Amino acid sequence: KLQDSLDAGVGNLVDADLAKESAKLQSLQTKQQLGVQALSIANQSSSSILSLF
Amino acid sequence: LNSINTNSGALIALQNLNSTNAELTQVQQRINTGKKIGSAKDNGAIWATAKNQ
């Protein structure tokens, strides 16, 4: 019984709760796609001044 | 007026373009970060309060 209790304590210390991790995965994938879109929009800024010459 | 040396209208158009470009880069920050208060520069009180909380 003491060995089972110690293993349960190690699991309480290190184990992650994956149910939070799934929502974090979805939100981070969406945030990465939005960040790539914002990075492309930032990369396009230089083009506008070529047309004014 | 009708002068070669000076063109005030281009200056006003350029400052207006600078304003719309600043609004654009701010919106790009709001998408790539996902936060309307991403730093102390945006609003120090709400930012410090959310940081402490």
Image (cartoon, coloured by chain):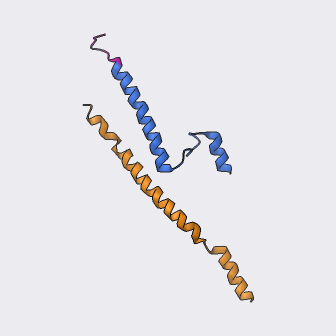
Chain colours: A orange, B blue
| Residue B3 placement, left or right of A22 | left
Residue at 38% x, 22% y is B12
The boundaries of the magenta stretch are: B1-8
Q: Is residue B5 magenta?
A: yes
Image quadrant holding the N terminus of chain A, namely bottom right
Q: Is residue B41 magenta?
A: no
Q: Give the left or right position of residue B3, taking residue A30 as reference.
A: left
Q: Is residue A13 left or right of residue A48?
A: right
Residue B37, quarter of picture: top right
Residue placed most toward the observer, B4 or A44? A44
State whether the magenta stretch is mostly helix, strand or loop.
loop
Position of residue A15 in the picture relative to residue A53 (left or right): right
Place of residue A19 in the rendered image (x, y in percent of width and height, measured from the top left): 58, 70
Residue at left 54%, top 64%? Answer: A23
Task: Work out whether B36 lies above or below A21.
Answer: above
Find residue A44 and report its horizontal and vertical position in percent: 33, 44
Q: Residue furthest top?
A: B1
Which residue appears farthest toward the right when viewing the image?
Answer: A2
